[PDB]
Length: 148
Ligand SMILES: [Zn+2]
Image 1 (tube, rainbow, N blue to C red):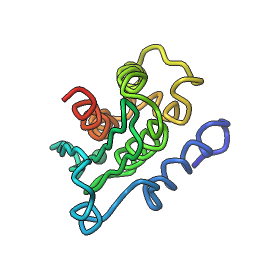
Image 2: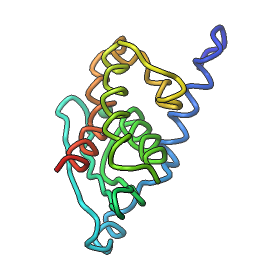
Image 3: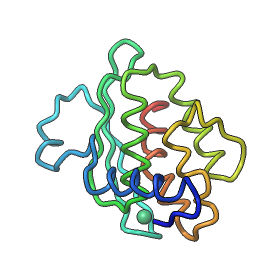
């Protein structure tokens, strides 16, 4: 929220606006009536209230629609949503790349702000305590849904 740095306040509205107004977050009503072309994975962390179910739909090697649902914090609802908007018409390869490249930046290592884009606000969550699993919980669910 501060304004000494240039990134901080701009980076702390992307989280606030993808957590109070997520783009791809559905209701438990809306999820049950989804077409059975969607796959699902629920991942839960015990370090927060983050228990999210992801929904991906494949159309000839291209992920066409991604939605997520459930309970989550700002770090979980922003990381999932921002990730969801970006994997939105990409292929089942070049998503598995973002996931591990995102995880390496979450693990405090090399990242490309051109490849990770608005996931680069999470570039130093390994410095905030017990927030690493909050920024991995929803993307690990996507990870399973791309492989299995
Ligand atoms: Zn959390």
